[PDB]
Amino acid sequence: SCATGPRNCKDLLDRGYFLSGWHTIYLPDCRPLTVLCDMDTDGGGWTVFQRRMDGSVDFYRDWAAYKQGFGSQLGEFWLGNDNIHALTAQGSSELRTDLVDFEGNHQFAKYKSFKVADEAEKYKLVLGAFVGGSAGNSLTGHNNNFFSTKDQDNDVSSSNCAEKFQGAWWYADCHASNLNGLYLMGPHESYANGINWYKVSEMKVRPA
Ligand SMILES: [Ca+2]
Image 1 (tube, rainbow, N blue to C red):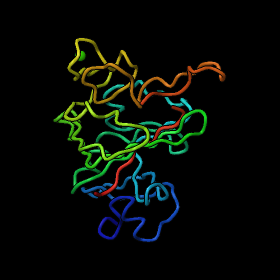
Image 2: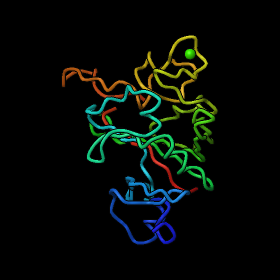
Image 3: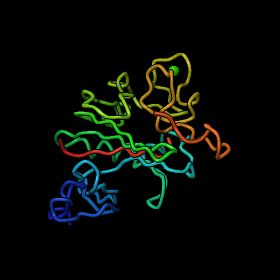
């Protein structure tokens, strides 16, 4: 039960769960949640809240969908903004992004602290300093921005960033598209495949 169950993937690693995969954790209000643990990357104990790999799941979804979460444990998913808030509520948390391009090259980015506020604060992003990574720093000008979806424009642009990129994100100005954008499905031989920060994305969190 909640009293003796784990709170996140770090707890699970401590209890001797050394393989990546889906496990039950208990949120701070004791709601059980099935989450994806990354037990291999950068010491392990990461809870994965976004994963894309093939563009099979539609990410151009409304506020309610992003709030609750959507997709498949067997594939691509967004864990849900209520859930991401719950995971980053207690204590301090670190963010990691892992990316794979179409030629098999692995890249990454790491951030000191990562919090998303509750729905009353439009799931505002509270992001710490870029700690480093080969993928580069793309979430630099995103700190303090509200979350935006197609039906809820909370950006600081005259346009609807979510519509214009076709995905939901903590948009400010929208000069480029993000990890939740269109997953291009063009000829296998061309550049017009994947997403921008390109074949694979994973966003994940761990106690700092
Ligand atoms: Ca706008």
